[PDB]
Image (cartoon, coloured by chain):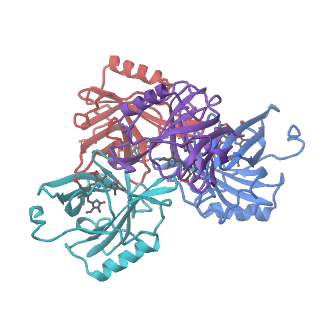
Chain colours: A cyan, B purple, C blue, D red
């Protein structure tokens, strides 16, 4: 199920979020079941933007070996709340993007929730600067999610095997 | 599935919508699969409000014979667009309510869609001032929906049988 | 003036706000300069609503003795933040209404800010269950506003002299 | 003044708007009174963005010869309405930006309105690819604004005299 009961949670975000250090490539390690990622080998590339915010380039290897991509823009509409962002993708409506925790150098936890009456629809990914994350960090970012309701048993481990994700090199 | 592909449509609404005549009791005849209606015998009661807009009282007979109810408030945030309303229910986030077509005296078609990136989540009900609607009107309000994408084959015919909905009298 | 430099602040609101004990009649003691109050002797009557939230009745005397009034509906769009309400006045667009402090029985502090780029337009009023309030309360509620950037030297003391306000039976 | 009575209009926008042909340098010819332009010789440079939308560079001369500038990002939040854009300027909150008419090669009409209860605050500018525009074009774009309530007698002609604007290499 993608519509989970209950309204959107209001989890804590990363304090003094430095977007400049958050830039670069991030590998999807574990993700909540979503409908936008239709393949595996997912990567998020955050690069510089001429105006405000940063740019977004997302890539995945579909099962047919085809690499699908989406471009987008990221802005924190409240500059005093830099970790709560709004992501504007192509052919898409504005979606929320909240950095809950990151070291900028190894791990990152991201959350998106849109309210639907008394139900909600959420997106979550555990990302790494490498195609793998230590199990300790995964178990700790999984506890941050369990703390505000997420069934960390619904999490899907994204395939990042070097031989399968070879077209993404 | 409750998350359908594609963004929210922008269908046409009832012209010169008179909310005063739309007040009263409406019976659910056919509805898109939703998560808020967990029973049958659904009824919508729109009554007067002391300030702006009108009040909302929704009732259904659950399978245990229990009548569940929800109260709410309805406001058209744009007075020059009176058919595009916002419904504020209890323990719920603000949801959209658009009257697409009504005679005020027999039939009414309602639509709610919230965007979720490149996907959407929608609610739809064909309502009648009586527990039944003629099949001609159902087939015509079903064509208005087919015209903007709705799979009118996903529609659920709400049970309004007099003997089963007897606790709602 | 009315459009002041700087984005809107996000002040703290009253905790465990009870809109039921907030119901009744509030008299304007002091107000930030605004464009909707074109008179004095102002009163805000918060009443009950059949649906969600409370009803609004705002009354004031103009310099020509005429009593002008407005009706509106008040709704907390997030039930988990019931002190951050939205006010839907007649012939008017949705405007914010935040109860920052209230003892329900004597005083209340209210703030409204809409963002206008790098500037803002704000409304704030100190209210009482009586046509007067003690200087100690006025001075502490002024210190709360001062903490978030409000020039308390721009505030205007509303006229609540029973002789001037005699048309308010 | 700046806060004018009445809610915001919903004017018509340019059809099949091409943001690519809209890119480049636009000079301010005439403008509605606003609080962000504190000088003259104004220019808006619309450039390319690595993600969604275009970049913004707004430049003006102050009475003291200093050239003040702002950077921002422009995004059409609804891809099916690309002429209704949102502008995210630096140190500023999201503000609306609507291209109502443009031939891309000579003229453009732009409007912004945020609602302030039963009042409103609006921004509008007539732009040219040259520091001047023909009276026939100015007069037709004034008639478009006049159709939706804009007092064209409040408009201000921006100074684009090459001698005064000499600091703009
Ligand atoms: C409910 C919230 C919600 C979010 C957050 C969201 C994001 C989002 N991700 C997308 C694609 C994508 N998103 C990713 C990857 C990621 N995306 C991430 O949020 C992160 C951190 C990764 C992980 C690396 C990839 C690889 C694509 C491209 C998929 C494709 O083109 O097939 C798109 C493009 C539209 C689409 O193809 O469906 C959107 C809007 N959509 C939503 O509905
Ligand atoms: C995606 C949009 C969307 C809408 C529109 C929506 C409406 C909505 N309908 C509700 C209940 C209800 N709604 C109805 C009935 C109706 N409801 C109607 O929209 C109409 C026209 C009928 C038909 C008569 C009933 C009977 C209940 C009470 C269900 C219960 O309490 O068990 C509630 C209360 C919260 C809940 O119990 O889930 C909401 C928010 N929720 C959404 O997520
Ligand atoms: C930027 C935010 C903002 C707010 C909050 C706002 C409220 C607001 N107050 C109004 C009327 C009014 N408002 C009040 C009274 C009050 N108002 C209060 O919120 C309180 C506490 C009092 C004081 C007791 C009165 C008396 C009127 C009617 C004035 C008249 O009709 O002459 C109206 C009706 C529109 C109008 O008459 O112009 C609005 C929208 N307007 C805005 O632009
Ligand atoms: C209510 C709506 C609204 C809008 C649209 C708006 C735009 C806007 N224009 C700005 C700067 C600016 N705006 C412009 C120029 C232009 N601006 C234009 O949209 C166009 C067409 C020109 C003219 C060519 C310039 C030159 C500056 C910088 C002024 C300076 O720094 O002194 C800023 C930065 C904040 C500031 O410097 O105060 C904003 C938010 N602000 C608002 O409040």
- Residue B145, position as x, y percentages in the image: 41, 33
Q: Quadrant of residue B8?
A: top left
Vertical placement of residue D54 versus D109, above or below? below
Vertical placement of residue B123 versus A150, above or below? above
- Residue B137, position as x, y percentages in the image: 48, 26
- Residue B118, position as x, y percentages in the image: 32, 47
Residue occupying the point 65% across, 45% down: B166
Residue occupying the point 47% across, 25% down: B136
Q: Quadrant of residue C168?
A: top right
**The N terminus of chain C sits in image quarter:** top right
Vertical placement of residue A168 versus B123, above or below? below
Q: Nearer the viewer, residue A63 or C4?
A: A63
> What is the residue that sits farthest to the top in this orientation?
D136
Say left or right for B96 vs A108. right
> What is the residue that sits farthest to the bottom in this orientation?
A136
- Residue D29, position as x, y percentages in the image: 35, 29
Inspect this view and state whether residue A92 appears.
yes
Residue occupying the point 80% across, 31% down: C64
Say left or right for D41 vs C157. left
Q: Nearer the viewer, residue A126 or B12?
A: B12
Count the labels in the image. 0
> Which quarter of the rendered image does ligand 3 occupy?
top right
Inspect this view and state whether residue A50 appears.
no
**The C terminus of chain C sits in image quarter:** top right
């Amino acid at each position: 199920m993608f519509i989970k009961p209950g309204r959107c949670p209001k989890p804590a975000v990363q304090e003094d979020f430095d977007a400049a250090r958050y830039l670069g490539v991030w590998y999807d390690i574990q993700r909540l079941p979503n409908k936008f990622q239709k393949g595996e080998c997912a990567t998020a590339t955050y690069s510089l933007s001429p105006g405000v915010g940063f740019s977004v380039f997302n890539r995945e290897r579909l099962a047919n070996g085809t690499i699908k991509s989406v471009i987008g823009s990221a802005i924190a509409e409240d500059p005093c709340e830099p970790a709560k962002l709004q992501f504007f993708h192509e052919n898409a409506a504005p979606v929320p993007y909240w950095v809950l925790s990151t070291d900028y150098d190894n791990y990152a936890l991201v959350y998106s929730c849109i309210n639907l009456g008394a139900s909600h629809a959420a997106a979550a990914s555990i990302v790494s600067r490498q195609p793998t994350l230590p199990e300790e960090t995964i178990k700790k970012l999984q506890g941050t999610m369990s703390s505000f309701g997420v069934g960390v048993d619904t999490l899907l481990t994204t395939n990042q095997d070097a031989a399968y994700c070879s077209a993404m090199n």
